[PDB]
Image (cartoon, rainbow, N blue to C red):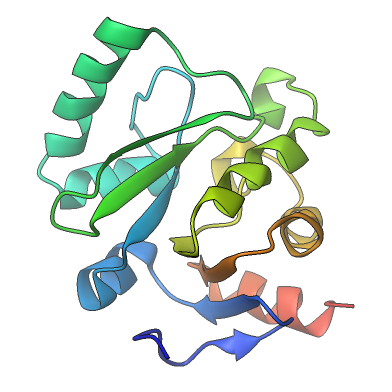
Length: 167
């Protein structure tokens, strides 16, 4: 049993809810929250900007030190950093950004990072300002992630379309 509430069950391991991931993280304090990161861990907008704002910029300060030591992530890659006030850990995952021309086949590689964690609160990778089709992102998630994933979808209209169209 876990703390996640109000989710629709899509599969054995994937759950979905219309929710603000920031407000959901603050309520649950999950072991892992996933950030929709870029390779520079520059948390300007979208999910990343909202998560970072909720940490009072402490996520960005920690991230800048990580990049100064390690250099940029790979598209499809990830790193584990602090979850600050939101979670124990934040898994920063880089999905391909269609608005930069990145290979959508890298979306499966991105979701494979989730399999290193037994339970996660996450957004749909490469959705929103990363430009991919969220219906596609949900299909790749279901077909790639084997651990227990609780998906937060900010937009009510999109949530209802994801559920209605789910095979």
